[PDB]
Amino acid sequence: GSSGSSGPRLYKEPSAKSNKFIIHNALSHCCLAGKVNEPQKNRILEEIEKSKANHFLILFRDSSCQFRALYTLSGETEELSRLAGYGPRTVTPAMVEGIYKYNSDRKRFTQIPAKTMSMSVDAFTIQGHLWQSKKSGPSSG
């Protein structure tokens, strides 16, 4: 026939590697650093503080194209929920074009060798067909 997909996973204790504080800075770093983003930045700094999330990602326009919207990573899965800003209510790892991290040692930005979510991430950019218009629909069965 024609079918076959993944399901459950292994079973290894969790690892508290929250990167919220790393983001709070990413904003004051440049993502949302500036007088023009003085009122917003705060709004973002709050949302995060208000949010009970530990992992926060920064949604850019395309290729570290400044900050567009903030999102939280679902510890239950790999999907991302829309925290604040303006974009897709949620974001899947299938739509994620690329992923990046934040050099907490060099205070810079880096890319991930993987296309999947991970605590070693601090920035991502959804696909391009998203912004553009064409079509949209789920897929599972």
Image (cartoon, helix red, strand yellow):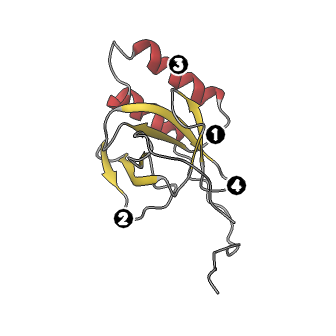
Task: State the CA–CA distance, disc 2 to disc 4.
Answer: 23 Å
- 85 shown above or below 115: above
* Residue on which disc 1 sits: 53
Task: State the CA–CA distance, disc 2 to disc 3.
Answer: 32 Å
Image quadrant in which you'd find residue 81 = top right
* Amino acid found under the numbered disc labelled 4: Glu
Task: State the CA–CA distance, disc 1 to disc 3.
Answer: 16 Å
Task: State the CA–CA distance, disc 4 to disc 1.
Answer: 12 Å
* Residue located 62% across and 82% down the image: 2
User: Local crowd at mark 2 within 10 Å, few (<14), some, or many (≥20)?
Assistant: few
Mark 1 residue element: loop
> Residue 92's spot in the image, x, y percent?
56, 52
User: Local crowd at mark 3 within 10 Å, few (<14), some, or many (≥20)?
Assistant: some
* Residue on which disc 3 sits: 43
Task: State the CA–CA distance, disc 4 to disc 3.
Answer: 26 Å
Locate the N terminus by quadrant. Answer: bottom right
Task: State the CA–CA distance, disc 1 to disc 2.
Answer: 24 Å
